[PDB]
Image: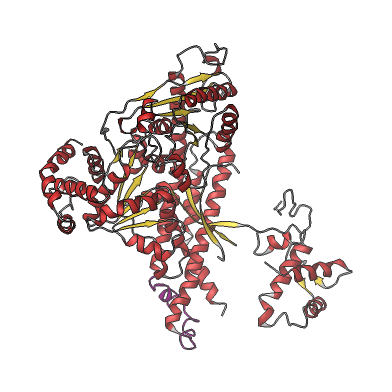
Amino acid sequence: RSRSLADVTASAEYDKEAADLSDEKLRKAAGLLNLDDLAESADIPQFLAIAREAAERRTGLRPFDVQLLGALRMLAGDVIEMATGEGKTLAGAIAAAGYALAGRHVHVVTINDYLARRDAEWMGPLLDAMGLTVGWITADSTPDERRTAYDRDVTYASVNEIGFDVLRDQLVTDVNDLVSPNPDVALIDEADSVLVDEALVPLVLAGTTTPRLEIIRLVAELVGDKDADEYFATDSDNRNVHLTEHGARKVEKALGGIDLYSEEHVGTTLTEVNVALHAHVLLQRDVHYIVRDDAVHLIWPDGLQAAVEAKEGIETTETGEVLDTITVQALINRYATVCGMTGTALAAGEQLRQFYQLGVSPIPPNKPNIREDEADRVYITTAAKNDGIVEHITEVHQRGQPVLVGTRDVAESEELHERLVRRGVPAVVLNAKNDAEEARVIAEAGKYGAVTVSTQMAGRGTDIRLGGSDEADHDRVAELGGLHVVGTGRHHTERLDNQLRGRAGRQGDPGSSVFFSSWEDDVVAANLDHNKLPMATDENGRIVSPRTGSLLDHAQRVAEGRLLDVHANTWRYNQLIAQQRAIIVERRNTLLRTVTAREELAELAPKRYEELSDKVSEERLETICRQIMLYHLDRGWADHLAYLADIRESIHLRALGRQNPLDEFHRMAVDAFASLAADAIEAAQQTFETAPTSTWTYMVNDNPL
């Protein structure tokens, strides 16, 4: 950041020239820049100057030397520490240009669908003025709309979509449908959240897995009377019951005069009959299956589970299996150069270096932040804290001063709404359902008598200005002391405390912040000794001893180290899974480039040579061979994840929470995978001998509902 600072001051030489340039010559000037050596390069001050001019010409806001050092430090592959109000959007977009002008293909990971579309339409003109093209991706945007957006020099999309696109590509039956592009440059917004907090969080691809009610009935009608219609095998008492001739003809006529043994019924009506009989006859509700909930268990052979489920009658569906999965961390490590920015970066520096091989470059502010931070107000009971929370807010509100309140949950922040409104305080809650609305609300959060209630991750990315979305109320709201942030308890990590605090002293304007903790709070609880805490109370519950900051701070530093120990022990598992997906996606690609047909034609090929002389088309044969090839690979790996997850749970439970290194997971996942590819070519071969419906994606969140 020492050479970079000099590279920012050098750009002054060109401010006169750039200002004299016509929109046309400016786009050509940028187009004539040698930045293949990224940040360090010769044409760097010239760029910073063109970036500054293009910005003032398009957007209007003349960038600061701090907003250029942010972008410049990002060009040098660092995660920057830039505060709220410092121009995170414009810094990243100037940074993105630098990378795109250098011939690269930038991905601007917003980790929010609203912010993605917003920042692409905001930055778009600036980049347009620089000959670069901007695209954006929402959940709704079609596969053609994705290809167009990905085609652009700079692409704005959430970590979920970028991920979901890598996953949805595992439903592709032909190359021309494939969406996701080669991951080159990742410029991550709010690097802190995405890379540290949400890293372990997996992105999943689930897909839906029906016999005759007419047959399950005919079989129940068959067993009911004095039967000699079915012959239950004795060559093994537990072996599949065969059908008698008398019984078959009952079934043959009951279904209106069909032959069970004709090609039309052989592998269909008969298997339906055979499966149903087995379940009805061989298995009974005593040491065979049992119920408990609304499902059948085993004290499954293809189609039997559902046949047992239709005998007892507990008719169920909604079974959605993991077809494919990837985690945030693994998806991010696929990029050649990862980049980023966040208000709170330093406090993660270790984990970013440890897992992403990324440094942190803290950027100073434009104007020194003069926000007043009060030490945590501590209470004995949780109710005593909640008590003081109301009385503080009311005193803050009555003066006029706007208030912002941070919470752990919805029901947590729900309880406060009722408590505040009843006391006279006009509040507003921010339930995570409408990001666009949340944003239109929060822009008016710095208004006279405004009282905004929010959870931990709500209203993110939208600046709270004084007097609403830019108003002359500023002068009044500044006199009152700016925005007043109120924490209703400390988070698992201090980064999140300072995120909230961060929303108040933007652009050297006044601001205030307070946190409310209690010896009853989940954080303190178990992660500290109860006996070691001050007990001395107030008439209103506040701990008398000011010696509280350090005992709370420590409690957190413990909880952080505990979560890091989980992250380290879990990534070790997630890494091997990823390494295997790498092997599966590799052979999935070669299979979408006609290797498939030559695989069968050289695998004995007694039927392939008969599917070439009596063929429909050898061109359609390549499309035929890949249906069977891919199917088995996709079905083979979807089953491996079903193993890996059951083996994972039958480890977590078989330890309760001892936090002991497994390694049982590794050796097993390795051995189970070893015989995957070899089994998939054989299982495909066996299907040539016999001459998905509704899939969705999701980000695995917490454990509530």
* 284 relative position to 319: left or right: right
As for residue 197 lying within the magenta part, the answer is: no
For the C terminus, the image quarter is top right
Q: Please, is residue 5 above or below residue 645 in the view?
A: above
Classify residue 128 by image quadrant: bottom left
Task: From the viewer's side, name the closer residue of 633 and 110.
Answer: 110
Residue 470 spot, x, y in % from top left: 36, 40
Residue 236 at least partly seen: no
Residue 51 spot, x, y in % from top left: 21, 48
Q: Which residue lies furthest to the right in this view?
A: 226
* 461 relative position to 607: left or right: left
Q: Residue furthest bottom?
A: 613
| Span colored in magenta | 592-616
Residue 688 spot, x, y in % from top left: 53, 76
For the N terminus, the image quarter is top left
The residue sitting at 52% across, 63% down in the picture is: 635
* 138 relative position to 647: left or right: left
Classify residue 419 by image quadrant: top right
Q: Please, is residue 6 above or below residue 176 in the view?
A: above
Task: From the viewer's side, name the closer residue of 491 and 436.
Answer: 436
Task: From the viewer's side, name the closer residue of 68 and 568.
Answer: 68
Main SS class of the magenta portion in the image: loop
Count of numbered circles in the view: 0
Render colour scheme: secondary structure
Residue 511 at least partly seen: yes
As for residue 606 lying within the magenta part, the answer is: yes
Q: Please, is residue 344 above or below residue 235 in the view?
A: above
